[PDB]
Amino acid sequence: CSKKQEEGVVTNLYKPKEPYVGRCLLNTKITGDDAPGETWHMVFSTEGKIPYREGQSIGVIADGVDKNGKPHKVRLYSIASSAIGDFGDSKTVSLCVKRLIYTNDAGEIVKGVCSNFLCDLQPGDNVQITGPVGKEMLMPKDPNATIIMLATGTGIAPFRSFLWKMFFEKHDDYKFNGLGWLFLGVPTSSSLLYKEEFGKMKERAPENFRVDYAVSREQTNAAGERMYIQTRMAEYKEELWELLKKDNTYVYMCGLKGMEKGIDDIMVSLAEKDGIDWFDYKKQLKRGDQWNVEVY
Amino acid sequence: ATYNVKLITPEGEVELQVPDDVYILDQAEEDGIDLPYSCRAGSCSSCAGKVVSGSVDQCDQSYLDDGQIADGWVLTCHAYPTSDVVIETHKE
Ligand SMILES: Cc1cc2nc3c(=O)[nH]c(=O)nc-3n(C[C@H](O)[C@H](O)[C@H](O)COP(=O)(O)OP(=O)(O)OC[C@H]3O[C@@H](n4cnc5c(N)ncnc54)[C@H](O)[C@@H]3O)c2cc1C
Ligand code: FES
Image (cartoon, rainbow over the protein chains, first blue to last red):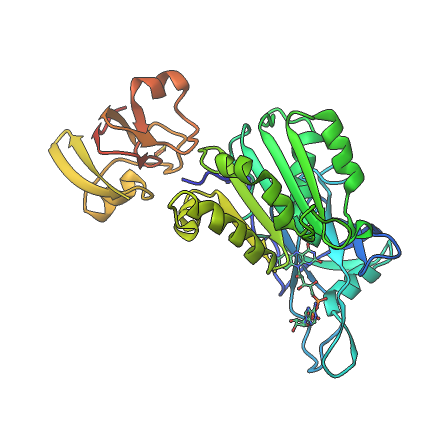
């Protein structure tokens, strides 16, 4: 019996063999001009033909062909908007896309194929979309849940999704009355994502929502340690650990893989303080839908 | 992980070992026991049983109200065991 949403969830209405063709409605850079790398927020039309749910992804199939003449493989992007969507009419889907550009060992500049196609979209352009995809990051059934959201970079996306539904929307069948606790880790302030929206959420539910930023290149603690997501977490170390002992606490983790390890190590020494092996406790939390990871 | 569910049918009394994540009907089916069922979706009466002792997780079924749930009505197609359980089957 899932402790996560299941009623009204659909997957794979569309597959790479025959994508849905939507339209770019808007596409906006949301990071500052001095960030290490651009992140863009973009909204596509779906004529309501893709009724996704908070937590899910869609695939994009970028135009053109690879080096061997085959069409490009789907790349997945976590849905950044709530089920009803940025326009609130249930006919749009939004993404939060990091433009991948990197220099390889040979000295060449390489452009990530789907991320640059997405980030290049003009309003009016056609996008080939598939999905919805995934059950793993669905929201808890429990409306009074403690939802702890651990994000790095574009891993804010499904949580932007959760939090829109929890705090910006009225729904007859869902009134969130738990604690939403968001941690978001980026390397610079200009890398921060949706700060203003979370600001608004903190304002209207101060008792139900918390947000903590961890900006590794601009923040330290007084021990001189850089503020990665795990080092921000360390400051609420026992509070979080208490919360984890509860029936109604669900942890979700989204973003770059390798965010994972730093967090485990904080948990490891929390666990040992109790005689407990963290990994036993973890896999056991997973079995109760309480530690949900989607990193990439 | 696994519980003993005793199934009291109009033909007597059977014992099953049901995993905590397999629906009771489904185990029943696996072990050759014929229980009535129709929607198999937790929104009709067809597989109605009654819990005589023990407890079930009925995973947000649609048919039974709180009153009835409180009375010990179970939808045997949509119920997981949360303990050792004795159910009376065939109960429309
Ligand atoms: C479930 C899921 C959800 C996701 N959600 C999001 C999201 O919300 N936002 C988002 O921006 N992305 C997300 N991604 C990642 C996304 O799917 C793509 O993998 C990413 O955008 C890169 O795709 P690309 O086609 O632009 O790069 P590609 O053309 O596929 O090239 C990537 C390849 O280049 C090499 N490479 C990749 N990254 C680097 C690097 N940093 N440095 C050096 N070499 C590298 C690797 O070999 C890699 O396989 C998600 C992925 C998954 C699986
Ligand atoms: S068969 Fe209809 S609810 Fe079990």
